[PDB]
Image 1 (cartoon, rainbow, N blue to C red):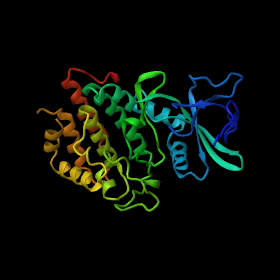
Image 2 (cartoon, rainbow, N blue to C red):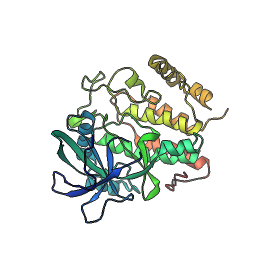
Image 3 (cartoon, rainbow, N blue to C red):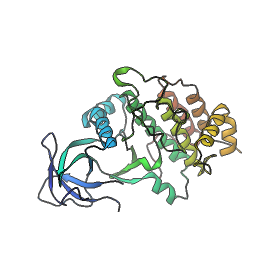
Image 4 (cartoon, rainbow, N blue to C red):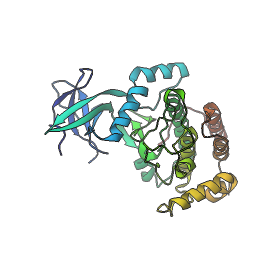
Length: 318
């Protein structure tokens, strides 16, 4: 199905006009997009349009997240109060309803990014430096604190969901909120239980123990997912990576390694970077409904940067 005629002008719900260009990268139904003008949408376009049938659940979930939490000025306000260089939550530009060939579709206009981190990781023989991992993780902690404080949990952090700013290789953004989860609607935390609405478990190698136990994701699970990403990034591996077809094996391993983090460090690393063990110990202390002390997690990571004779200079080193 072609959802658009290439070069057509589409008008969103706020009457802003956009033009549609070609598909990106040979992701889903995602096309380059720009402000309506007399020029064609070029390969250096600054936006994308994501389009799915209107009965698609994930696009609707994602749209709601972006409308509630990613409004250009909502993000800018947070950046000013927190004295952040930037925030890696993509900006929402608009959305609408588009009918074609008697089918109804939903569309959403978003920032356009450069490469995902997974491609860059594979081009570096599946390693990121200690400097890179700490700098990424600091910015992901900023992002997670933001979304959590706006009642959502991502539940699927991974290098393929981390995109670089098209104009700035040192700024990383977390994308894909189609299976994001509003753990705290109206300040009321979800109970330790399954959500019948939700069916997703994250990505098996990175997902949280809570997710493996069949309960809805919460804040600690996001921090836990980031922990496993860090190890994967530093080492090229996770202990359970050859048994991903067997979830109960993966859960058993995660549960045992949480109970004994020094054995995780022994398995994954001779000498391990101490911030990682410290990070995971702090995450382990969290109850299901407990608010993380994000600034203490960031501190733990800053002490890793000090230990390699560096600082938080915002350099990803990719």
